[PDB]
Amino acid sequence: GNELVRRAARNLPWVVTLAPEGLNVYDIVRTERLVMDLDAWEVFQNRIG
Amino acid sequence: MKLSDLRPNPGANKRRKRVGRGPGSGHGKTATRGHKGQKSRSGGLKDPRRFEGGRSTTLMRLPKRGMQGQVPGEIKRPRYQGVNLKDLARFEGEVTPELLVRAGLLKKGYRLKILGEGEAKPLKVVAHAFSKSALEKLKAAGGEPVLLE
Amino acid sequence: MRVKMHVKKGDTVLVASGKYKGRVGKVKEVLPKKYAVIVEGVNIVKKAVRVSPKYPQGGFIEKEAPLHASKVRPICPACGKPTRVRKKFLENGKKIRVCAKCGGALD
Amino acid sequence: PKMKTHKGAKKRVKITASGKVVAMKTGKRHLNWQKSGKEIRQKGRKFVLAKPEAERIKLLLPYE
RNA sequence: GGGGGGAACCUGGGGAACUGAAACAUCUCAGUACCCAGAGGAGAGGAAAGAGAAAUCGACUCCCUGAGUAGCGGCGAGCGA
RNA sequence: CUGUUGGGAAGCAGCGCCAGAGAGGGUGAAAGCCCCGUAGGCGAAAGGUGGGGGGAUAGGUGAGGGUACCCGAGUACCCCGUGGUUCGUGGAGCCAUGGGGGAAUCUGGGCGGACCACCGCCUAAGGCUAAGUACUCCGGGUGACCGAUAGCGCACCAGUACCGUGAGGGAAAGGUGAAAAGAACCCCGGGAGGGGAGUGAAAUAGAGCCUGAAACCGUGGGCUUACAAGCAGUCACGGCCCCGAGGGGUUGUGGCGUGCCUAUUGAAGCAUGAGCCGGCGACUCACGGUCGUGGGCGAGCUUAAGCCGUUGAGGCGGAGGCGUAGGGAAACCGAGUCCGAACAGGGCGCAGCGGCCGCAAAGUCCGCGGCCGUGGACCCGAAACCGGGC
RNA sequence: GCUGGGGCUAGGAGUGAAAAGCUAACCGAGCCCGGAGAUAGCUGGUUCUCCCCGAAAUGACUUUAGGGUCAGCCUCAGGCG
RNA sequence: GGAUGACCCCAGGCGGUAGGGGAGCGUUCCCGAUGCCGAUGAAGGCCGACCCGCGAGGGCGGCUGGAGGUAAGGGAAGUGC
RNA sequence: ACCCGGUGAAAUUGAACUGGCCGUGAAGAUGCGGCCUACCCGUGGCAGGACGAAAAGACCCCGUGGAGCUUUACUGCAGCC
Ligand SMILES: NC(=[NH2+])NCCC[C@H](N)C(=O)O
Ligand SMILES: [Mg+2]
Ligand SMILES: [Mg+2]
Ligand SMILES: [Mg+2]
Ligand SMILES: [Mg+2]
Ligand SMILES: [Mg+2]
Ligand SMILES: [Mg+2]
Ligand SMILES: [Mg+2]
Ligand SMILES: [Mg+2]
Ligand SMILES: [Mg+2]
Ligand SMILES: [Mg+2]
Ligand SMILES: [Mg+2]
Ligand SMILES: [Mg+2]
Ligand SMILES: [Mg+2]
Ligand SMILES: [Mg+2]
Ligand SMILES: [Mg+2]
Ligand SMILES: [Mg+2]
Ligand SMILES: [Mg+2]
Ligand SMILES: [Mg+2]
Ligand SMILES: [Mg+2]
Ligand SMILES: [Mg+2]
Ligand SMILES: [Mg+2]
Ligand SMILES: [Mg+2]
Ligand SMILES: [Mg+2]
Ligand SMILES: [Mg+2]
Ligand SMILES: [Mg+2]
Ligand SMILES: [Mg+2]
Ligand SMILES: [Mg+2]
Ligand SMILES: [Mg+2]
Ligand SMILES: [Mg+2]
Ligand SMILES: [Mg+2]
Ligand SMILES: [Mg+2]
Ligand SMILES: [Mg+2]
Ligand SMILES: [Mg+2]
Ligand SMILES: [Mg+2]
Ligand SMILES: [Mg+2]
Ligand SMILES: [Mg+2]
Ligand SMILES: [Mg+2]
Ligand SMILES: [Mg+2]
Ligand SMILES: [Mg+2]
Ligand SMILES: [Mg+2]
Ligand SMILES: [Mg+2]
Ligand SMILES: [Mg+2]
Ligand SMILES: [Mg+2]
Ligand SMILES: [Mg+2]
Ligand SMILES: [Mg+2]
Ligand SMILES: [Mg+2]
Ligand SMILES: [Mg+2]
Ligand SMILES: [Mg+2]
Ligand SMILES: [Mg+2]
Ligand SMILES: [Mg+2]
Ligand SMILES: [Mg+2]
Ligand SMILES: [Mg+2]
Ligand SMILES: [Mg+2]
Ligand SMILES: [Mg+2]
Ligand SMILES: [Mg+2]
Ligand SMILES: [Mg+2]
Ligand SMILES: [Mg+2]
Ligand SMILES: [Mg+2]
Ligand SMILES: [Mg+2]
Ligand SMILES: [Mg+2]
Ligand SMILES: [Mg+2]
Ligand SMILES: [Mg+2]
Ligand SMILES: [Mg+2]
Ligand SMILES: [Mg+2]
Ligand SMILES: [Mg+2]
Ligand SMILES: [Mg+2]
Ligand SMILES: [Mg+2]
Ligand SMILES: [Mg+2]
Ligand SMILES: [Mg+2]
Ligand SMILES: [Mg+2]
Ligand SMILES: [Mg+2]
Ligand SMILES: [Mg+2]
Ligand SMILES: [Mg+2]
Ligand SMILES: [Mg+2]
Ligand SMILES: [Mg+2]
Ligand SMILES: [Mg+2]
Ligand SMILES: [Mg+2]
Ligand SMILES: [Mg+2]
Ligand SMILES: [Mg+2]
Ligand SMILES: [Mg+2]
Ligand SMILES: [Mg+2]
Ligand SMILES: [Mg+2]
Ligand SMILES: [Mg+2]
Ligand SMILES: [Mg+2]
Ligand SMILES: [Mg+2]
Ligand SMILES: [Mg+2]
Ligand SMILES: [Mg+2]
Ligand SMILES: [Mg+2]
Ligand SMILES: [Mg+2]
Ligand SMILES: [Mg+2]
Ligand SMILES: [Mg+2]
Ligand SMILES: [Mg+2]
Ligand SMILES: [Mg+2]
Ligand SMILES: [Mg+2]
Ligand SMILES: [Mg+2]
Ligand SMILES: [Mg+2]
Ligand SMILES: [Mg+2]
Ligand SMILES: [Mg+2]
Ligand SMILES: [Mg+2]
Ligand SMILES: [Mg+2]
Ligand SMILES: [Mg+2]
Ligand SMILES: [Mg+2]
Ligand SMILES: [Mg+2]
Ligand SMILES: [Mg+2]
Ligand SMILES: [Mg+2]
Ligand SMILES: [Mg+2]
Ligand SMILES: [Mg+2]
Ligand SMILES: [Mg+2]
Ligand SMILES: [Mg+2]
Ligand SMILES: [Mg+2]
Ligand SMILES: [Mg+2]
Ligand SMILES: [Mg+2]
Ligand SMILES: [Mg+2]
Ligand SMILES: [Mg+2]
Ligand SMILES: [Mg+2]
Ligand SMILES: [Mg+2]
Ligand SMILES: [Mg+2]
Ligand SMILES: [Mg+2]
Ligand SMILES: [Mg+2]
Ligand SMILES: [Mg+2]
Ligand SMILES: [Mg+2]
Ligand SMILES: [Mg+2]
Ligand SMILES: [Mg+2]
Ligand SMILES: [Mg+2]
Ligand SMILES: [Mg+2]
Ligand SMILES: [Mg+2]
Ligand SMILES: [Mg+2]
Ligand SMILES: [Mg+2]
Ligand SMILES: [Mg+2]
Ligand SMILES: [Mg+2]
Ligand SMILES: [Mg+2]
Ligand SMILES: [Mg+2]
Ligand SMILES: [Mg+2]
Ligand SMILES: [Mg+2]
Ligand SMILES: [Mg+2]
Ligand SMILES: [Mg+2]
Ligand SMILES: [Mg+2]
Ligand SMILES: [Mg+2]
Ligand SMILES: [Mg+2]
Ligand SMILES: [Mg+2]
Ligand SMILES: [Mg+2]
Ligand SMILES: [Mg+2]
Ligand SMILES: [Mg+2]
Ligand SMILES: [Mg+2]
Ligand SMILES: [Mg+2]
Ligand SMILES: [Mg+2]
Ligand SMILES: [Mg+2]
Ligand SMILES: [Mg+2]
Ligand SMILES: [Mg+2]
Ligand SMILES: [Mg+2]
Ligand SMILES: [Mg+2]
Ligand SMILES: [Mg+2]
Ligand SMILES: [Mg+2]
Ligand SMILES: [Mg+2]
Ligand SMILES: [Mg+2]
Ligand SMILES: [Mg+2]
Ligand SMILES: [Mg+2]
Ligand SMILES: [Mg+2]
Ligand SMILES: [Mg+2]
Ligand SMILES: [Mg+2]
Ligand SMILES: [Mg+2]
Ligand SMILES: [Mg+2]
Ligand SMILES: [Mg+2]
Ligand SMILES: [Mg+2]
Ligand SMILES: [Mg+2]
Ligand SMILES: [Mg+2]
Ligand SMILES: [Mg+2]
Ligand SMILES: [Mg+2]
Ligand SMILES: [Mg+2]
Ligand SMILES: [Mg+2]
Ligand SMILES: [Mg+2]
Ligand SMILES: [Mg+2]
Ligand SMILES: [Mg+2]
Ligand SMILES: [Mg+2]
Ligand SMILES: [Mg+2]
Ligand SMILES: [Mg+2]
Ligand SMILES: [Mg+2]
Ligand SMILES: [Mg+2]
Ligand SMILES: [Mg+2]
Ligand SMILES: [Mg+2]
Ligand SMILES: [Mg+2]
Ligand SMILES: [Mg+2]
Ligand SMILES: [Mg+2]
Ligand SMILES: [Mg+2]
Ligand SMILES: [Mg+2]
Ligand SMILES: [Mg+2]
Ligand SMILES: [Mg+2]
Ligand SMILES: [Mg+2]
Ligand SMILES: [Mg+2]
Ligand SMILES: [Mg+2]
Ligand SMILES: [Mg+2]
Ligand SMILES: [Mg+2]
Ligand SMILES: [Mg+2]
Ligand SMILES: [Mg+2]
Ligand SMILES: [Mg+2]
Ligand SMILES: [Mg+2]
Ligand SMILES: [Mg+2]
Ligand SMILES: [Mg+2]
Ligand SMILES: [Mg+2]
Ligand SMILES: [Mg+2]
Ligand SMILES: [Mg+2]
Ligand SMILES: [Mg+2]
Ligand SMILES: [Mg+2]
Ligand SMILES: [Mg+2]
Ligand SMILES: [Mg+2]
Ligand SMILES: [Mg+2]
Ligand SMILES: [Mg+2]
Ligand SMILES: [Mg+2]
Ligand SMILES: [Mg+2]
Ligand SMILES: [Mg+2]
Ligand SMILES: [Mg+2]
Ligand SMILES: [Mg+2]
Ligand SMILES: [Mg+2]
Ligand SMILES: [Mg+2]
Ligand SMILES: [Mg+2]
Ligand SMILES: [Mg+2]
Ligand SMILES: [Mg+2]
Ligand SMILES: [Mg+2]
Ligand SMILES: [Mg+2]
Ligand SMILES: [Mg+2]
Ligand SMILES: [Mg+2]
Ligand SMILES: [Mg+2]
Ligand SMILES: [Mg+2]
Ligand SMILES: [Mg+2]
Ligand SMILES: [Mg+2]
Ligand SMILES: [Mg+2]
Ligand SMILES: [Mg+2]
Ligand SMILES: [Mg+2]
Ligand SMILES: [Mg+2]
Ligand SMILES: [Mg+2]
Ligand SMILES: [Mg+2]
Ligand SMILES: [Mg+2]
Ligand SMILES: [Mg+2]
Ligand SMILES: [Mg+2]
Ligand SMILES: [Mg+2]
Ligand SMILES: [Mg+2]
Ligand SMILES: [Mg+2]
Ligand SMILES: [Mg+2]
Ligand SMILES: [Mg+2]
Ligand SMILES: [Mg+2]
Ligand SMILES: [Mg+2]
Ligand SMILES: [Mg+2]
Ligand SMILES: [Mg+2]
Ligand SMILES: [Mg+2]
Ligand SMILES: [Mg+2]
Ligand SMILES: [Mg+2]
Ligand SMILES: [Mg+2]
Ligand SMILES: [Mg+2]
Ligand SMILES: [Mg+2]
Ligand SMILES: [Mg+2]
Ligand SMILES: [Mg+2]
Ligand SMILES: [Mg+2]
Ligand SMILES: [Mg+2]
Ligand SMILES: [Mg+2]
Ligand SMILES: [Mg+2]
Ligand SMILES: [Mg+2]
Ligand SMILES: [Mg+2]
Ligand SMILES: [Mg+2]
Ligand SMILES: [Mg+2]
Ligand SMILES: [Mg+2]
Ligand SMILES: [Mg+2]
Ligand SMILES: [Mg+2]
Ligand SMILES: [Mg+2]
Ligand SMILES: [Mg+2]
Ligand SMILES: [Mg+2]
Ligand SMILES: [Mg+2]
Ligand SMILES: [Mg+2]
Ligand SMILES: [Mg+2]
Ligand SMILES: [Zn+2]
């Protein structure tokens, strides 16, 4: 959810950036690794609950 | 697991039947329509559910029965839906129309009638009507039937 | 509204690509419509001319052929290096081209 | 556009709980004087439409 | 002040037929196509002599739904709140 | 930035660097850092707009009591003819009104589907009123949209040429190259055209220009052919030529042998269609249904319009739909119900696998597929009918 | 009587010493554009490959007879055995 | 058999129009892809007596061509004359 | 008309390496069988055949196709009473 973090990483070829409200399986399956905020991990657990 | 692994199960996505695409396919030329006649034509036949070649139809030779109604239409009257004792088994304490609505048991806009199938439970059940047997069973099981007006 | 030209007649430019890459020369002409520049003694071609009043004896003449303007980089009059151009606003408060490597005016 | 219900069928026929199609027996609308009581009585019942005809009629009642 | 124009859109005044009903006339197509008048960036509608059964709602317009229900119908084909 | 191959580097190699910018288009080939841009920011003296903010102004405002003055007229209302509505004369109300008759001012009047009573609802015969809605000539953004027979009729000087008295109809036609460096000059020729020279990485890239298929025409070569009977091939063998116990080409002789498609009981058929070649050319889509099927959940399954977010991110939203009970024209009753006097008889209905667990399943949602309904619904084709114009 | 020029009458309409003649080179109903992709139970056409199975040209009814609905006969899935 | 489309062995079926079913090939476009093939030559064209495939096709090689093409695995259609 | 110089169409055309008889064949065969005849290629001529070309027979029937016309067919409408 940190905009500053997303802005810094977004232009990297190997990085896809998302706010946790936007977590979706296409973007997960597209990428080799998943990296999340504890905060993001939390809204995720709320979403799948 | 990546994109090149994402795959439907066998049978989930099947190929279409394509006709009029050659001898080898089994569906060339006439495109599975046979030779001539109305059915082979673009636009085809009259409705097969009804039409019978000009003869008076199976349907139309049967008699009408009953009240069909008339303008200005449906007469408003209170409507009942029955829910069985067995369907009440999941509840505790007090059951009411709104609760049965919410549970997906009772449809909105319907008055509630309790029916005799299944076993009664000691519950206070609030309803617009009861079958005789529903009434008997609920008393015997120690429940409290409350009748609305 | 207007074609953006980072180079003008007749600053000194490096020809950064093509057969004449590495070459340096003054910009003889700028042709915005073709997005091209003419650079002195760069991109020489042999042109056939008819025996005419303009060319008695006829034969051939040498001509500078236009260069795609992106192939060309201005040379900083200050630090003498090929550079991209920046805009700087003066007190005037006009705007000028300035070198990117140092900060000198290119005019 | 969605299928329309055939009202001619809806007025003559009913789909039972197991998907049978039931209609009134024909032949007692009139000319009854010389028909035996057995004929009148038995024609006063419903009957189950033969399967091929029932399927056709059901298709006319998509929202029953 | 008016006149005339504007791709569709809009409202009003008029308004078919093929076709469908496996013929055809009621019916359908369809108040559609089209003609005309007018409007404007929209137009129409609009502040209950409404709804219609809730002891209820609260202008009008528009979308979802109600619902292919209620009904209408050579109770046919179909039409349809 | 350098080196390197190359006509050319952006390719490859070495060493770097930017990134709130690695969308995309260019540059001699394939470039984040060369160019135009992109992310992020900045900008109007003039004219337009201004639904947002601020301010004026117009307008806005009590209580009982009595009085019964007013409260939209050829109107309501009734009848006749008709329209609108789901309502086609129907028990036919309501709303509208062409004709006739023709009121009342709240103790007045219209409505709740003939009518009457009761009970309610509402205030006709004057007018205006943003917004949410529709459209796309215009500008922009974006495509599991087209790529010159496609996509608009038009990529190009097209509503043109041309056709028609006119209304009206209505085309074809895109590409040299990186750069014109678009071939000076000489040679044959009246010119056209060509041969040299020359430019170019390339000139069968030379302007009648990218690629350059096929029909079709020609030149050269190999095999073959003037005693032979043929859907033209095929099987065999032999001859010659070619490439080097094999193969390719050709075909002398011998065997066998009734084109293709369509339509038909039946066609080589003297039945249809086709000169040949290239390109265009016909079973689709939406919504609904019905089966099957791949999953999700399961007495439950599922959301629609919207709303928030995103800017190729997803979520919220339960209104509603299907299912959970049937039977009866219905009142109604209900695991039953209807017919019946019946407690008769009959019709239509009613009841998982394993050690609480799992599993499976009603059902339902979504995807996929077959087929059906509605639309032009596989494509092409009438003769005609109608409307408005010429 | 013929003829120049200037005019009027047109689509179910004109005009016709009448032939259903003529109304812009085909008139028992002009032409153009539109409804419109009218409708066509008729004729034609319907495009890659391989594999398994494999019909009918009957019966009933049909303003039906060269078209249909149902049955029969083919095929595929599940079930029974 | 072996346990499961691993391959082998024995056996039997395999003419086919309307038509049913099954399995595949190829075309355009999307994901894969900020990748990968590509001027030491893309696509397209012309040959081939070679390789794989039952076949539709797919490789490979020579020539042409001169700037694009696009895998395994999936998705969608203006998809084969 | 014919020949030489100049310019140079057309309908038609599955492809053709396109003979006779007697047969056969969907019943009138260059194309099938048997036999007979026949060196290869033209030019001017003739029309018996190619069921020669042209025109999706205008006769005839069929289509619940169309149109013009009629009437004591049906049902309307103008117009008149
Ligand atoms: N908030 C975000 N990071 N959104 C997704 C990235 C946005 C943008 N499409 C990008 O890739 O640069
Ligand atoms: Mg990105
Ligand atoms: Mg990124
Ligand atoms: Mg990625
Ligand atoms: Mg991304
Ligand atoms: Mg699909
Ligand atoms: Mg489909
Ligand atoms: Mg299949
Ligand atoms: Mg296919
Ligand atoms: Mg095929
Ligand atoms: Mg098949
Ligand atoms: Mg078949
Ligand atoms: Mg065929
Ligand atoms: Mg057909
Ligand atoms: Mg079929
Ligand atoms: Mg089929
Ligand atoms: Mg079929
Ligand atoms: Mg057919
Ligand atoms: Mg047939
Ligand atoms: Mg047939
Ligand atoms: Mg056919
Ligand atoms: Mg037939
Ligand atoms: Mg037929
Ligand atoms: Mg048929
Ligand atoms: Mg047809
Ligand atoms: Mg059609
Ligand atoms: Mg039809
Ligand atoms: Mg009959
Ligand atoms: Mg009803
Ligand atoms: Mg009503
Ligand atoms: Mg209690
Ligand atoms: Mg500037
Ligand atoms: Mg360079
Ligand atoms: Mg250098
Ligand atoms: Mg200035
Ligand atoms: Mg009916
Ligand atoms: Mg009866
Ligand atoms: Mg009776
Ligand atoms: Mg009676
Ligand atoms: Mg008797
Ligand atoms: Mg008796
Ligand atoms: Mg009796
Ligand atoms: Mg009785
Ligand atoms: Mg329903
Ligand atoms: Mg139900
Ligand atoms: Mg005016
Ligand atoms: Mg105006
Ligand atoms: Mg109107
Ligand atoms: Mg008016
Ligand atoms: Mg009107
Ligand atoms: Mg109108
Ligand atoms: Mg009219
Ligand atoms: Mg009609
Ligand atoms: Mg029609
Ligand atoms: Mg219709
Ligand atoms: Mg119909
Ligand atoms: Mg009809
Ligand atoms: Mg019909
Ligand atoms: Mg008729
Ligand atoms: Mg009609
Ligand atoms: Mg209508
Ligand atoms: Mg319109
Ligand atoms: Mg106007
Ligand atoms: Mg607006
Ligand atoms: Mg208004
Ligand atoms: Mg008011
Ligand atoms: Mg409902
Ligand atoms: Mg209507
Ligand atoms: Mg090179
Ligand atoms: Mg070099
Ligand atoms: Mg370099
Ligand atoms: Mg590098
Ligand atoms: Mg970006
Ligand atoms: Mg880019
Ligand atoms: Mg780029
Ligand atoms: Mg690259
Ligand atoms: Mg690329
Ligand atoms: Mg770039
Ligand atoms: Mg910006
Ligand atoms: Mg900007
Ligand atoms: Mg007041
Ligand atoms: Mg007062
Ligand atoms: Mg008074
Ligand atoms: Mg009033
Ligand atoms: Mg007045
Ligand atoms: Mg009236
Ligand atoms: Mg009406
Ligand atoms: Mg009425
Ligand atoms: Mg009625
Ligand atoms: Mg009414
Ligand atoms: Mg009343
Ligand atoms: Mg009235
Ligand atoms: Mg009146
Ligand atoms: Mg009152
Ligand atoms: Mg009163
Ligand atoms: Mg009234
Ligand atoms: Mg009234
Ligand atoms: Mg009312
Ligand atoms: Mg009432
Ligand atoms: Mg009253
Ligand atoms: Mg009211
Ligand atoms: Mg108004
Ligand atoms: Mg407002
Ligand atoms: Mg407005
Ligand atoms: Mg508005
Ligand atoms: Mg809009
Ligand atoms: Mg636009
Ligand atoms: Mg394309
Ligand atoms: Mg493209
Ligand atoms: Mg073209
Ligand atoms: Mg075009
Ligand atoms: Mg082309
Ligand atoms: Mg076009
Ligand atoms: Mg245009
Ligand atoms: Mg065109
Ligand atoms: Mg064009
Ligand atoms: Mg032109
Ligand atoms: Mg003309
Ligand atoms: Mg002209
Ligand atoms: Mg025309
Ligand atoms: Mg070029
Ligand atoms: Mg060029
Ligand atoms: Mg180049
Ligand atoms: Mg000369
Ligand atoms: Mg000379
Ligand atoms: Mg010359
Ligand atoms: Mg020469
Ligand atoms: Mg020359
Ligand atoms: Mg040279
Ligand atoms: Mg080279
Ligand atoms: Mg080359
Ligand atoms: Mg070449
Ligand atoms: Mg070339
Ligand atoms: Mg090029
Ligand atoms: Mg060329
Ligand atoms: Mg050429
Ligand atoms: Mg030769
Ligand atoms: Mg001899
Ligand atoms: Mg010889
Ligand atoms: Mg032979
Ligand atoms: Mg032999
Ligand atoms: Mg050999
Ligand atoms: Mg051979
Ligand atoms: Mg040989
Ligand atoms: Mg032998
Ligand atoms: Mg033969
Ligand atoms: Mg034969
Ligand atoms: Mg063939
Ligand atoms: Mg044919
Ligand atoms: Mg035939
Ligand atoms: Mg025949
Ligand atoms: Mg025959
Ligand atoms: Mg023959
Ligand atoms: Mg022949
Ligand atoms: Mg014939
Ligand atoms: Mg023939
Ligand atoms: Mg025929
Ligand atoms: Mg031809
Ligand atoms: Mg040919
Ligand atoms: Mg072709
Ligand atoms: Mg289909
Ligand atoms: Mg479609
Ligand atoms: Mg569909
Ligand atoms: Mg389906
Ligand atoms: Mg499904
Ligand atoms: Mg689920
Ligand atoms: Mg849910
Ligand atoms: Mg519903
Ligand atoms: Mg019922
Ligand atoms: Mg009774
Ligand atoms: Mg019973
Ligand atoms: Mg029973
Ligand atoms: Mg489950
Ligand atoms: Mg399921
Ligand atoms: Mg079906
Ligand atoms: Mg349609
Ligand atoms: Mg159509
Ligand atoms: Mg269609
Ligand atoms: Mg269809
Ligand atoms: Mg005509
Ligand atoms: Mg008519
Ligand atoms: Mg008529
Ligand atoms: Mg008429
Ligand atoms: Mg007219
Ligand atoms: Mg005179
Ligand atoms: Mg005169
Ligand atoms: Mg005159
Ligand atoms: Mg005159
Ligand atoms: Mg006239
Ligand atoms: Mg006159
Ligand atoms: Mg006129
Ligand atoms: Mg006419
Ligand atoms: Mg007319
Ligand atoms: Mg007429
Ligand atoms: Mg007349
Ligand atoms: Mg005369
Ligand atoms: Mg004319
Ligand atoms: Mg004439
Ligand atoms: Mg006529
Ligand atoms: Mg004429
Ligand atoms: Mg028009
Ligand atoms: Mg129409
Ligand atoms: Mg047509
Ligand atoms: Mg017709
Ligand atoms: Mg087809
Ligand atoms: Mg078999
Ligand atoms: Mg039969
Ligand atoms: Mg029958
Ligand atoms: Mg019969
Ligand atoms: Mg007949
Ligand atoms: Mg007969
Ligand atoms: Mg027929
Ligand atoms: Mg059948
Ligand atoms: Mg059998
Ligand atoms: Mg079966
Ligand atoms: Mg089976
Ligand atoms: Mg077989
Ligand atoms: Mg199978
Ligand atoms: Mg494929
Ligand atoms: Mg293909
Ligand atoms: Mg695309
Ligand atoms: Mg990509
Ligand atoms: Mg790429
Ligand atoms: Mg590479
Ligand atoms: Mg090469
Ligand atoms: Mg391509
Ligand atoms: Mg190949
Ligand atoms: Mg190649
Ligand atoms: Mg490129
Ligand atoms: Mg390819
Ligand atoms: Mg690809
Ligand atoms: Mg793949
Ligand atoms: Mg995928
Ligand atoms: Mg197509
Ligand atoms: Mg001579
Ligand atoms: Mg001559
Ligand atoms: Mg031949
Ligand atoms: Mg011969
Ligand atoms: Mg004989
Ligand atoms: Mg013959
Ligand atoms: Mg013979
Ligand atoms: Mg012969
Ligand atoms: Mg032969
Ligand atoms: Mg033979
Ligand atoms: Mg023979
Ligand atoms: Mg012979
Ligand atoms: Mg012989
Ligand atoms: Mg002889
Ligand atoms: Mg001769
Ligand atoms: Mg002759
Ligand atoms: Mg002659
Ligand atoms: Mg012959
Ligand atoms: Mg002859
Ligand atoms: Mg003859
Ligand atoms: Mg002929
Ligand atoms: Mg003729
Ligand atoms: Mg004819
Ligand atoms: Mg024809
Ligand atoms: Mg004929
Ligand atoms: Mg005929
Ligand atoms: Mg005649
Ligand atoms: Mg006749
Ligand atoms: Mg006949
Ligand atoms: Mg006839
Ligand atoms: Mg008839
Ligand atoms: Mg018939
Ligand atoms: Mg008729
Ligand atoms: Mg007629
Ligand atoms: Mg007529
Ligand atoms: Zn400097």
Image (cartoon, coloured by chain):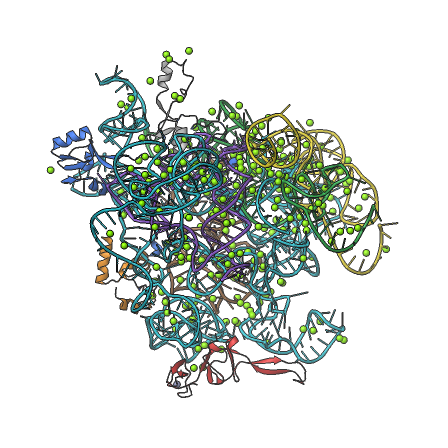
Chain colours: A orange, B blue, C red, E purple, F cyan, G green, H brown, I yellow
Q: How many numbered marks, from 0 up?
A: 0
| Residue placed most toward the observer, B143 or C70 | B143
| Residue placed most toward the observer, B8 or F112 | F112
Left or right: F130 as drawn, with respect to F204: left
Horizontal and vertical percent position of residue C28: 52, 84
Horizontal and vertical percent position of residue F228: 72, 43
Horizontal and vertical percent position of residue F260: 60, 42
Left or right: F173 as drawn, with respect to C90: right
Left or right: G42 as drawn, with respect to B17: right
| Residue placed most toward the observer, F346 or C100 | F346
Above or below, C38 against F231 in this view is below
Tell me, yes or no, if residue D3 can be seen here: no
- Residue at 36% x, 15% y: name it: D38
- Residue at 12% x, 32% y: name it: B141
Horizontal and vertical percent position of residue F280: 55, 52
| Quarter assignment of residue F197 | bottom right
On the rendered image, what quadrant is the N terminus of chain A found in?
A: bottom left
